[PDB]
Amino acid sequence: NALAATNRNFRHASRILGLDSKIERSLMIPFREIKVECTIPKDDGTLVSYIGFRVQHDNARGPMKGGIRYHPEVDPDEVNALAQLMTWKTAVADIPYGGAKGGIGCSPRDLSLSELERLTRVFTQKIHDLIGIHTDVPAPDMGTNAQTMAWILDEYSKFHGHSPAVVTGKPIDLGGSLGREAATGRGVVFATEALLAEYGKSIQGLTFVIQGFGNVGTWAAKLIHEKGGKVVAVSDITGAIRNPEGIDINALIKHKDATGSLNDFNGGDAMNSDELLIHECDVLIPCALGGVLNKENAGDVKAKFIVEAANHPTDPDADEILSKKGVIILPDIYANAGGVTVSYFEWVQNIQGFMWEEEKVNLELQKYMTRAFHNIKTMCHTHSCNLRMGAFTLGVNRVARATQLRGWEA
Amino acid sequence: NALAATNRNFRHASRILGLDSKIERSLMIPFREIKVECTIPKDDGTLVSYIGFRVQHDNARGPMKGGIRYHPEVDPDEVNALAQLMTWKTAVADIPYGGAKGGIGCSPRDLSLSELERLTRVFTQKIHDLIGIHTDVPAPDMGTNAQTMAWILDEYSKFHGHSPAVVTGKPIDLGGSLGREAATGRGVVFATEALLAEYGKSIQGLTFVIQGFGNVGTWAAKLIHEKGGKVVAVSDITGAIRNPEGIDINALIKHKDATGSLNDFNGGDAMNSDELLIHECDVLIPCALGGVLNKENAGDVKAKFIVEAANHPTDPDADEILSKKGVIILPDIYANAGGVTVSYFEWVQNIQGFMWEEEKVNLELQKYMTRAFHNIKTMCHTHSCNLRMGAFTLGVNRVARATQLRGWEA
Amino acid sequence: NALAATNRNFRHASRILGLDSKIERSLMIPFREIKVECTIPKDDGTLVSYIGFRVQHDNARGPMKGGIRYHPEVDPDEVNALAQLMTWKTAVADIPYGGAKGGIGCSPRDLSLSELERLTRVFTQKIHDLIGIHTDVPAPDMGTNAQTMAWILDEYSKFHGHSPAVVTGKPIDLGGSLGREAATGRGVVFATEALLAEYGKSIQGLTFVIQGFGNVGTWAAKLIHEKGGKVVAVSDITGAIRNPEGIDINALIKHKDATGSLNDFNGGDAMNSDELLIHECDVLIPCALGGVLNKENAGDVKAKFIVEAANHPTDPDADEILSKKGVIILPDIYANAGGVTVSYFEWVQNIQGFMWEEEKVNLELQKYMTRAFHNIKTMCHTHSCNLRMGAFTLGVNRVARATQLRGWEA
Amino acid sequence: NALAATNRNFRHASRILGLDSKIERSLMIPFREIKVECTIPKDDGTLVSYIGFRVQHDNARGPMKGGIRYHPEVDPDEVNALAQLMTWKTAVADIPYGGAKGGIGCSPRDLSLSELERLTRVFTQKIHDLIGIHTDVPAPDMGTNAQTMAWILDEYSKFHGHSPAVVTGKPIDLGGSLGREAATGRGVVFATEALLAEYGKSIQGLTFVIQGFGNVGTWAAKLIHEKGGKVVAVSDITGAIRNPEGIDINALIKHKDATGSLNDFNGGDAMNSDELLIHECDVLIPCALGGVLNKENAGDVKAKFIVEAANHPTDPDADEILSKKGVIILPDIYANAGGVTVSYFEWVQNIQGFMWEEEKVNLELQKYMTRAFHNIKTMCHTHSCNLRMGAFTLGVNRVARATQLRGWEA
Ligand SMILES: [Ca+2]
Ligand SMILES: [Ca+2]
Ligand SMILES: [Ca+2]
Ligand SMILES: [Ca+2]
């Protein structure tokens, strides 16, 4: 379901642009795919063998960027789709990168710390000559954290000398960047502000309904409340609360710290966990799950702006229903692009050898998001479509233009 | 059918040797697999994209060796099986190599000469950092000839300087080896001589029935007739002849040069093309097709020695029927190993910078084949099996021993 | 004629500085010269062979910088002179570069696009190990444009990995720099402003006569008119106009867009194309051809400041006549140095991995030009000469000082 | 005069072979040419600058081979001609090499030992990345000896690690080869024996007239006398002797050791130094100077076989006069090829890491010379020409065949 959205959108964007068939066929085939065998001895002494993989889609615009995934179940079609999506997303945000995706087919909940370190180091030894500073830059993903990036950096340094810029997401004392934890919420807030200012409104004095308190949800809620807006509904995996005149987010954060839930809050009454999506509001921000909007919920919603901060929260039929209603949906390919931009900033800081302060990071992030939205709006106006197809058209056009400009060996 | 024989034989050989399960699992997983995209402009100007692949099984004993195939239809299971078979075959012949297999999914009958050269050069540019003199040595295969090796050598030299030993099968004036065309027939004759001398007989004064006149068939027939034997039946794709007192091979070769068939020969009468497999003879040598022996033909044959110079000419049920009859079958994993041995000799000559004469090549080939047969006979006597399982046991034992000796990262 | 000016100026500058003869002899001999053969198949199939060349003068101060020229007629003396001139010019502008010059002896008007791409790629393959990021950075020249730099970048990346900083002048979406088109006019305006402010005057309220509308001429005219000056005479290859109270440049630019000439303009009357060089004016700026000032015109001119924005517009006898008259001539070695400075900025941006905005580029350009003029004025005051010999003395002194500081192998 | 012979012979050989014009044009242009500046401080402290050069003609058959020359006067045309001649000569002898030639424009009679070492080391540092084991192998020439090769080896080893095979002609204890001093005389004797055995005669019982006692002359005379022939006339720079029944060479060698001349010998009477070229003899061997045969001497000679052991001893008109007379001339491109063959053997021994004995060297040299003569005779019979054009045709054909086989980038 998540792999068909990307390729359907690509076909539609290619139809809009009138691309040549040969160029589209060339944009289907990935630049390279690799499978290697990783065999380690356990703590007992016995051997265990896994299979590691790496897919690299395009490099027409610069180095390749992508995450390393530690999950037992893998599928080549899903991995190819994810690599292609990373390519388009990087093209949209206008950072000089490509797309990639890799991982190991193992379950990290069964291995101790030492075995996990051995597995990471062996994987790095096997793929050391296919990554690099200007070739391919791994990043952490699910099943992976900053410690794994530290181990990868250590092994690659053993091979090619001290290269701090080969990975992103490192700890702070190994060359990490400030402002990583709040990047996605900052990006969502900046995108929402730009979208609102397009129509002449502003964040100050509007109504927001936020679904979830992951990092994205809590940071977006805190930033919105600081800006001057009022939030009237909050969800979670366990519980949901409402307040018609605004919820004190600063109090709610410390309430969740101790209680661990949203039950028995002070400034708000509990509500059913299936109705907040239909509340009266100005902006609706889903941040937890994808596909939560479908045919049944499509007719009932009465929001005026939807910001897709999650991964694929909207189905196509619901999208057409909402288009006929008259609401505006910001695509997820652009809304949650704060993380990749901050990773690019960290890569730049490591290349330069000099670290920035947090203010510089935030200003650069704001500038990049605003410029991206202006470009997407112009491209949407040129071809007379909606925002999603504007984004995909812009990305595909950039990549195709670079590919044809670079050359075809005569 | 051809991919199940190799893995069934591996399972049986592992059962005989009592190998650990972990080591067998490690011997299943290939060392590396690669897919790349090769896009070229045609003579008109339009673009065409193909997908090239390369599988590298093991390198526990030295560099990797394998062929490049230009065939429209590909299958990962078949390619993996072929790479594994090359690994075992190299282990049997006792040359310091591993196993690999690669190719391009295109039909060379539709491309002109210039387009074919462009395709080869682009493929080499894409896989240049994964092959080498002591890493992986490509060889020609079906759809490929010596000119392709010349082009590969040229491009790799552009990248890494003059490296004549990166490929085998080059033309004679680019660093090729003498005695390449007659290698397989020489090997078959040497193996047959060793097998006969095992039981006390000799080639001089026996009866041979040879199926086919490819290079292998004609060279084996000529060498056998020179040695002192008599051949009494000859086949082809079109026609088959017989002579109870021996056929003049030296005359038959020039007869086929002009007529182009075996019809209306002087010293021999025509025969049905489905009965020669049941002729009275001492040695039967199939050289054209595989699977030609099955249940129907198994009971009728009355030969005393079968030499499998082709690829998989015997089915398992036929093999057991023949074992109960009491005949001896030389496995094809060992009989047709002349080509790889001569390729190894060419690699050695290019490493040394000094070319050998033909006599030295022939003496070395004879020594290697005799030593291989003595080793296979000893290993067959140790475990009380037949010749085929002796060969496979010897190969698997060598590879496993090297792998465990090399180390497991503690 | 253009090759004797540079070496005569070098001899005079060496005489002024009192340089050792050994050091001068060492500064004559170029660091390296290379000739290679470039053979390609045409679209028909037939072969064509050309000869490519590259001269690298000095590298005492950093990497080497120079242009690639596609012209049928070549001469080693001219190429050596151009490389030496680039060395001195880079030394004057105070950017850490050296000097070089290369090209191919072919006529690009006879080759199609595909053949031209093949020629560029083959040339790059032949000289790939003699250029680099910190070794030698090619730039476009006449017969060459940004597409050729894209092809060179592609081939060099195939060899040494992604290296965007190996060439300058790339397209914008491949890593180009903003503000390239207006660099030379900006530089001329900044130099003129500094020269005027030396004597206490200012651009606001003076009279300018500009010869030509190439990029340099139109940009200088537009910037001068914006600053507050008035232009009273304009030339072209076809036509010339005059207006005693100032010409609306903003209107003239759009007039030339449609009409394609300067005839029948609104705010100005046509004039003879051989008299504007003798108009009453404060500043005279030739921007089209060289050598336009000679003995006949030397006595007639009545300007107070001459800014040589073209290549060698003044002859020596005319220079001495003008010196006796009492006018001031800004040398061309310094006036048109905007292009190399902006190319250096692009190289820096590609090294850092982060692109600048246009304002930063313009501020840095202004700072560099002002500092260069102050240095040249100080050096001119030290030795009691004019501006041209001050420039050449400064450049030669910098290069000699670096060479002697670096060492002579004891 | 010496540069026109080679190119005239090339034109004639191309006319005989019917070569394409494009291929001939491609065979004119050298692969690469390099000029560098070599500046050293003298023993006093003052600086001296020279210009070093290196020309590399072709590498279609393997590494490049050529000599380093220390002579004050240089000429690009002469150097190009010498490189081309080395290419053809290597092609004739059938060793896998190309052609090159380099040197320094200095007079070694004015520099002390330390300054000469400094010059050699600086030259090596400047051209270190353009030579190598499989790229280009320098050799000593006039103005150069084995000590210079030792210094070059030392510097190149400092750069790229211990590489004993980068130069040939090293001292014996640094990896030199046995049998170097007598290589050319051995080669001349072997060639003469093959030429005589072509017509049915033999060396035993013939008459020889040898002009000169350089290394070639003395070694050829000693070997011929040992074989069973009789020498009846000997020349030198100072003096000439004759004996109708044979001269004791073993006594003459020790006579020259003490006296230092050929005057007052025991077994032979003095003769005029301008008549021995017209003596009655079977074989005439000039070994000292070139061009000694011309129109005046052409009609007077009465020999039956001429072996050109020197460099260009025969003029074209004299050649046609001698052809009409009916004598046979062995070309110098083949007669004196012993040195390059022994240098190739030394290169092979250094590549292998194991030194040969003298007997193996002599046997290999004999085999190579005999095979070369048989090939030249066959090629001469095919096209119905004389021996010289047979040699040049064979060389050009080999080089062109390799070039077209290697490829043209489609
Ligand atoms: Ca692609
Ligand atoms: Ca394995
Ligand atoms: Ca110099
Ligand atoms: Ca050439």
Image: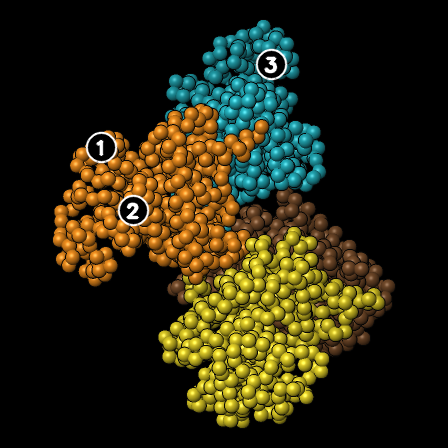
Chain colours: A yellow, B brown, C orange, D cyan
The amino acid pointed to by label 2 is: Ser
Q: What residue does disc 1 label?
A: C325
Q: What residue does disc 3 label?
A: D247
Q: Quadrant of the N terminus of chain B?
A: bottom right
Q: Residue at x 62, y 78 (%)?
A: A250
Place residue C376 in its image quadrant: top left
The amino acid pointed to by label 1 is: Lys
Q: CA distance from mark 3 to mark 2?
A: 101 Å
Where is residue D312 shown, x and y percent of the image? Answer: 46, 26
Q: Quadrant of the C terminus of chain B?
A: bottom right
Q: Residue at x 60, y 92 (%)?
A: A274
| SS label for mark 3 | loop
The amino acid pointed to by label 3 is: Ile
Subunit under mark 3: D
Whether tag 1 and tag 2 are in contact, CB under 8 A, the answer is no
Residue that extends furthest to the top in the rendered view of this protein: D264
Q: What residue does disc 2 label?
A: C202
Name the front one of labels 1 and 2: 2
Place residue B53 in its image quadrant: bottom right
